[PDB]
Image: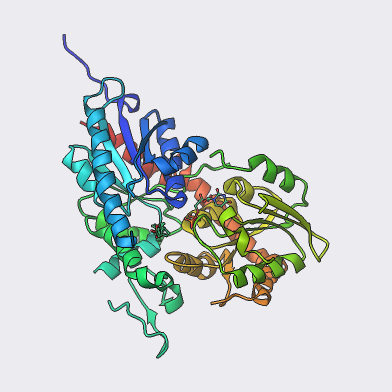
Length: 439
Ligand SMILES: C[C@]12CC[C@H](O)C[C@H]1CC[C@@H]1[C@@H]2CC[C@]2(C)[C@@H](c3ccc(=O)oc3)CC[C@]12O
Ligand SMILES: O=c1ccn([C@@H]2O[C@H](COP(=O)(O)OP(=O)(O)O)[C@@H](O)[C@H]2O)c(=O)[nH]1
């Protein structure tokens, strides 16, 4: 005689709340996909202005007001609005009868105040970092070593535990934001203000990729490396168009070019890249967002070209990046080195030409070229066509490039192993799921 009680994923409710930008939404969506496939009930909370985006990419979906002035006011409003918004949702779900009450809130690492919403309403908090471990620990040391730089007087090289030496150009780039550099800096530093009170510290990376620094952070804070959250081999826009075009190219013949969802290049920088791509011995697929089309050399959603070299080019406002990168036609990836684009390239075996723009993109580029050895970084600040030309020859037409390709194929296998049964990332994500079930 008695009652047995069963705690299983299908009666466990996970809340997820990304920062409303595609580089933060996308990795969180993939993680929600993996968690739902384990049987969990997953509710994704997102701002109204990103809601339609996420709806088209798909899991229960909740919208909250955008919550929005200069950078500082814009952001204090944002933090205040989403605090009460998300708190309301937790409480509606705690009294609801359909879904189970929330057990945990997975929130973006850049919204650390959400840990206080989670704990203030009696549920657990998991902080999802969308940056690699290596650059993240740079933010921690900065929050805690002199990082000022009078780059005009002398060159400095910084040594930190479990990191390669970092030149000034390898540190995170904040001066780009000029007046707002301090704001962007504090946003990334403050990720660590409560690192000791977080119930789960989640990183979208895999241990073999960052083993030295992952271990150092595992010792300090017991982090969980659970990446890549994207699947091995999201409904994005223009899928059929780009897949048909790529299906019509020769294998290993296409340079894929994209600077992500936020970065905006000067008109002179666009002219340089343009002139390189139209004279290279390769086809190209170049994503230029609608908002950036007017900065192209003197607006249609896409344009087709026969290049001066007799090759074929496609300029298009958006593509399915993961599908593009895994297409056999792609020879290499000219990228701003956002972490999602970097980790997607790694998981796809595609070598890179690094054109980093700001924040962690400079550090990622350093690791792409000198640590993982799967790409080369351009040298500035304007990057001229001849410099872009040099990097294409090196990646795509050289013995060194064949080696870079070999290195990328190795890392592709290692990230597949990480997310497969018994891999470090599969194990860490199962640690997260299983301990959510504990009494
Ligand atoms: C958070 C952010 C992306 C991820 C990483 O932490 C680096 C950050 C860079 C700065 C921040 C971006 C996000 C968009 C901005 C708010 C967006 C912006 C700028 C001005 C404004 O009024 O509203 C939004 C453009 C860039 C942005 O300011
Ligand atoms: O044409 C494109 C360009 C980018 N992305 C996606 O945009 C996301 C985030 O980009 P990233 O982190 O590299 O840099 P950001 O856009 O934040 O600057 C990635 O998941 C990419 O797959 C896409 O789907 N199609």
